[PDB]
Amino acid sequence: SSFNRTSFPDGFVFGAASSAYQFEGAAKEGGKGPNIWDTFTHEFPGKISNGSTGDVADDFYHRYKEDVKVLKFIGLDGFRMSISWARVLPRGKLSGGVNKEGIAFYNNVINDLLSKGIQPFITIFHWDLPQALEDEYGGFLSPHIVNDFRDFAELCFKEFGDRVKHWITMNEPWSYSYGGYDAGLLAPGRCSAFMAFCPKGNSGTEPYIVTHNLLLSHAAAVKLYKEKYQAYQKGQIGITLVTYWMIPYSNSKADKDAAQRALDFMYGWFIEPLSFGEYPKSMRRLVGKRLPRFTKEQAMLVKGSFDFLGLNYYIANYVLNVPTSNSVNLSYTTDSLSNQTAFRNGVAIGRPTGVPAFFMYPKGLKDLLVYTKEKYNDPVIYITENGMGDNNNVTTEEGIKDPQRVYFYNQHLLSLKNAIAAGVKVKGYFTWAFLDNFEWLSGYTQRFGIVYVDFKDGLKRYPKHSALWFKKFLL
Ligand SMILES: *[C@@H]1O[C@H](CO[C@@H]2O[C@@H](C)[C@@H](O)[C@@H](O)[C@@H]2O)[C@@H](O[C@@H]2O[C@H](CO)[C@@H](O[C@@H]3O[C@H](CO)[C@@H](O)[C@H](O)[C@@H]3O)[C@H](O)[C@H]2NC(C)=O)[C@H](O)[C@H]1NC(C)=O
Ligand SMILES: N=C(CCCS[C@@H]1CC(=O)N(Cc2ccccc2)C1=O)N[C@@H]1O[C@H](CO[C@@H]2OC[C@@H](O)[C@H](O)[C@H]2O)[C@@H](O)[C@H](O)[C@H]1O
Ligand SMILES: *[C@@H]1O[C@H](CO)[C@@H](O[C@@H]2O[C@H](CO)[C@@H](O)[C@H](O)[C@H]2NC(C)=O)[C@H](O)[C@H]1NC(C)=O
């Protein structure tokens, strides 16, 4: 006898997650065109650990049949995966033509998943923007992205919507904006010149520009799905957001307010437009005219534009107030006057993982969910990512034994259970990740999978103890 799925609601969806650039490989194969991550990893090897790329990744593009067998072996209800925009539309625009070989790959994966009784949860956009669109008008820096995003979504609805019943417009627009345009840590790698880190950009203005267009693009796809496809395809559409849970470093009003500002700027930036059609008051106050306004039309489009909310949860941080100052480092990051740290009084917020900044704090998952329920009218929620990373610095034999990850999932699922007990309408949960994969700026130095991938020996797959723990949990 042990903790198992019967403790969760009937029909609850347990799954594992993936994304196209991180898993697929075949970056220049099967008619696929270039995307901004091809470009970023090739042109800035200094920004990826060991100068790695997703050229091959897990080679999920060729190995998907064997991988789907692993999903079935674990016994999962669902699988979260994304569509490579430049694989299906190599020139970004619909008028640039649809790549039949790219459509065929996703159809093949979906049909195999369904034969195993696994529901595909499809992320339309997981950061891999076609280089053609980045080149033409600067990608999400331009309002032109909205119409092209809408057409890409429509292509997905038309080709896959007869079988796909859960759509996620985009993964973590916070990450795309902050990482791509404030810190320059992610493609397209833009930031202010004073950071001496990116060729082009403005960390004080571009993140706000990009976030606005991310929201409008999302809203365009949702409007189209609901008005044209939802009634006869009978699916649901949402968006995946990420936030840290923010804890005041001390009991002071200063730190309490700082914690809420940090949450406002990371989470509220997206969930308040989605819920209320406006940005958080703190952002309006502190960012001023660098923060775009929603026109009345835009607000109507964005407000209420989700059937469900996808939430990605990894960590919590303590937050300190940062006093105003005279030194002029203009950025989205410094705009919130907040400072996050994993340590209080010299003590870490939880158990360590193989990722330096990341400690275990399962309580924060429930805290986030209750906060979301209470502030945003009790939405339907899927946990679309939750997981931990190991440092890739031991043998295959050792990496497969991951009691730390078994511990991680036991504690987080117990916390999730308590959130459901508190009335949060959670309907599903997805492990990041299915396989050890290309972890963006960290390359292959960090392993998040419940399944091990031996990159040094034919990309061979081996279920970890965590996979076997889930297998048992899922009966
Ligand atoms: C699937 O899981 C259920 C529930 O598991 C319980 O709740 C989870 C949230 C975790 O905290 C688990 O650690 C916890 O056990 C299992 O049913 C439960 O089995 C336990 C025994 O392991 C029962 O506790 C015992 O009950 C007897 C009386 O029958 C007492 O004499 C014992 O001292 C002890 O208290 C528990 O009552 C029971 N709960 C329910 C709701 O039935 C279930 O066995 C498991 N299934 C499989 C196949 O593993
Ligand atoms: N990685 C992110 C957010 C990137 C934000 S920009 C910058 C880079 C980064 O990882 N960190 C921290 C972070 C990590 C995860 C979530 C939020 C914030 C940043 O703030 N989100 C999810 O995390 C998953 C695990 O991300 C790893 O987290 C630890 C990092 O060291 C590693 O590079 C990253 O790939 C990704 O694989 C998913 O594709 C993605 O949806
Ligand atoms: C492999 O990487 C892990 C993770 O970085 C190392 O374990 C960490 O060691 C540091 C330094 O002593 C500690 O501060 C952390 O608490 C450890 N993290 C854990 C255990 O999750 C490990 O030492 C590395 N091993 C080798 C051989 O390099």
Image: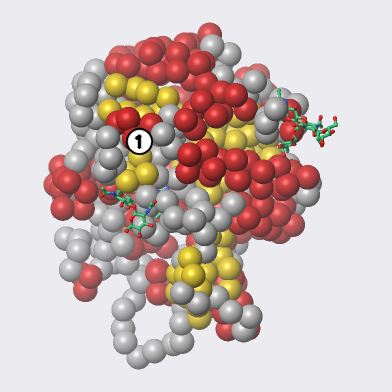
- Which is more toward the observer, 332 or 386? 386
Instruction: Work out whether residue 471 can be spotted.
Output: yes
Name the image quarter holding the N terminus: top right
190 relative to 123, above or below: below
In the image, residue 148 lies at what x, y percent? 39, 37
In the image, residue 327 lies at what x, y percent? 31, 87
The secondary element bearing badge 1 is classed as helix
In the image, residue 356 lies at what x, y percent? 36, 57
Q: Residue at x 25, y 54 (%)?
A: 189
Name the image quarter holding the C terminus: top right
- Which is more toward the observer, 76 or 403? 403
| Number of marks | 1
- Which is more toward the observer, 409 or 76? 409
In the image, residue 262 lies at what x, y percent? 52, 68
Query: Are there few (<14), some (14-19), or many (20+) residues within 10 Å of tag 1?
Result: many
Please state which amino acid type lies under the numbered disc 1: Gly
Q: Residue furthest top?
A: 115
Give the side of residue 50 with respect to residue 421, left or right: left
Give the side of residue 76 with respect to residue 49, left or right: right
Q: Residue at x 46, y 74 (%)?
A: 346
Q: Residue at x 42, y 51 (%)?
A: 353
**Where is residue 15, by image quadrant?**
top right
Q: Which residue is mark 1?
A: 399
Give the side of residue 349 with respect to residue 129, left or right: right
103 relative to 152, above or below: above
